[PDB]
Image 1 (tube, rainbow over the protein chains, first blue to last red):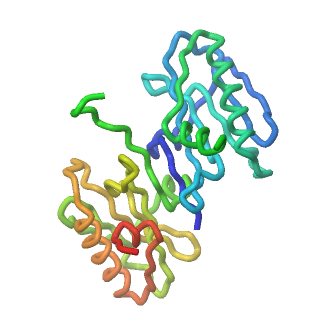
Image 2: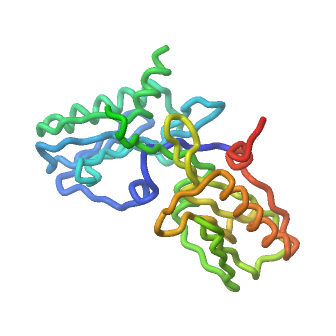
Image 3: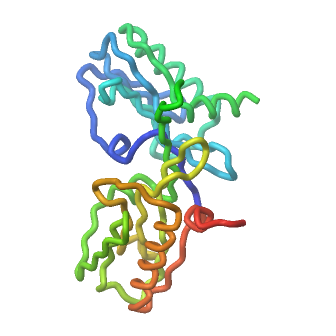
Length: 122
Length: 127
């Protein structure tokens, strides 16, 4: 029985979104997506992770939200679910932040992502 | 960083996104307002093994309030639900425990066997 810990409400996780100016990248076992039309915004990354024995284990879904609440980016596992490491996730997050910063967006990460980053580099 | 600062809620859930977002309906609807919570179930369902799964908000690393509970058959169908009243008046662990008890009795009338997730029973203590 897996459990999931998330920064996102159900509505934030289930909402459809699209990219006006699409940019995508396969980053090993993870897919990174972002909208290049987005500029000069404050953006927060929010994640959903599987939990196993009180530890954040597998990334299920990450989405980037503007302060007004629009989805402007996403990282997700390839649907074949090949499996990924903590390093794959940290690498993909840094790559997404770099891409969003190009258009002078300021990007921050949720406490869940901070925990994952911290406990992975222990 | 003040004494009034409302902290960010995270959510801990037994359910996948599809389990939580899936629509459902009742062939024989049955509802009860149980204090601050709404209980719904399908009276048509019989002879099933059912599991209760929940999504709780987490504040300061503690389970705070029930956001959504759903009852699932072995085949994965939703046959019951407990959710906060639309007005979100606030509720206690005891309100949740009572509503769960009420839902389980209701589902047992038709010879369904009901079990609860690890999260739910942990929320009711005490191991």
